[PDB]
Length: 326
DNA sequence: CCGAACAAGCATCAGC
DNA sequence: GCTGATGCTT
DNA sequence: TTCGG
Ligand SMILES: Nc1nc2c(ncn2[C@H]2C[C@H](O)[C@@H](COP(=O)(O)OP(=O)(O)C(F)(F)P(=O)(O)O)O2)c(=O)[nH]1
Ligand SMILES: [Cl-]
Ligand SMILES: [Mg+2]
Ligand code: NA
Ligand code: NA
Ligand code: NA
Image 1: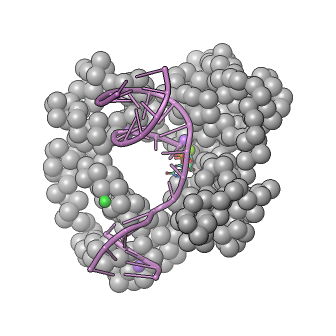
Image 2: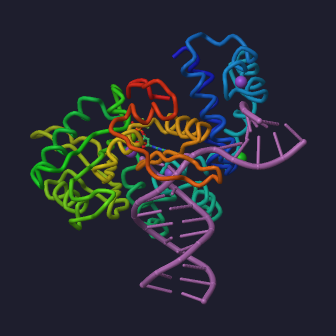
Image 3: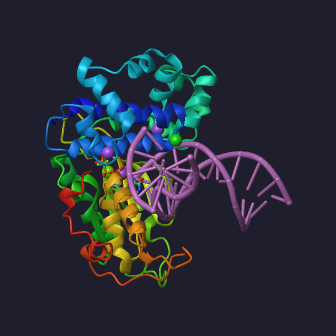
């Protein structure tokens, strides 16, 4: 990582703007700059050089100049001394606590891990499980454990119904040597954009993974999206594995390619691609790509039979998953 | 100089 | 109950 | 905060 110092600084600023300032556009600005710099294949010498990259403007260039000169940023040094800022930033590391809840907790004097544990009653269900596994959810998953988790999920799904197809997406499908969590796309032929010929399709899968004690907790769950907690089983007298976040998304079978594009990411890659789509007169979600009419309203779904078809519409050359880690 | 910035599922709350 | 806004999340 | 128009 040639410019690891610059990107870490930009990421820390992004987090500050999101968590503390609640300034989502500054947050996006910093992450996009950190992403474009992370991709830049030279050791950045000056803010003016970085300013040549799209998404690095005048203000970020100045901060890069300060950082390259001193090794630090005064703005961040002050932010780190501010206790309300530091407390808010920290509390948002719990799954289910965002900038609003973090500021509300700090208002009531709840501002440390111990404060949170003292006040479980003050947490909704998601936050409670996020606190329970706070330590574990900060751990990365080695690709070897990802493969074991993959083998479990695909085989249990096959046992519910041989016609399910479960695809692990996220950073795993992008070839990552480690992942932050497990993302599972799910399809079944009974659920298409035309009809739902079978209720409980996601539920049946969740229930089976719970039965075999893979899924241990639920953060949120509806008919198409499950967000929860899982754990690899461990061998005799082995220390147990950390608990892991798992997301399962049931998507209409005929819309698999938009779904797998969405769920493979990265999140910034999706933003950049959907932004380019609009500039090309299309709008992309996890279901369809549609033209924008003269008005501005999306037209009817365009035919898609591959990921590359989506790339073609917006006049991008196909990028393999491993080149979408933006 | 200024407006647009990706898109959406689930939990939660206020209002009716 | 439903509708719609908001928080939080992918 | 950045960009395009
Ligand atoms: N259009 C958007 N798509 C988004 C967004 N966030 C996530 N996603 C998509 C893409 C992720 O890869 C996919 C899974 O979301 P996830 O947060 O698990 O990201 P990744 O798996 O890519 C990862 F961060 F690298 P990890 O640490 O988990 O290994 O969900 C978003 O804000 N907009
Ligand atoms: Cl903002
Ligand atoms: Mg993931
Ligand atoms: Na630039
Ligand atoms: Na959080
Ligand atoms: Na995920």
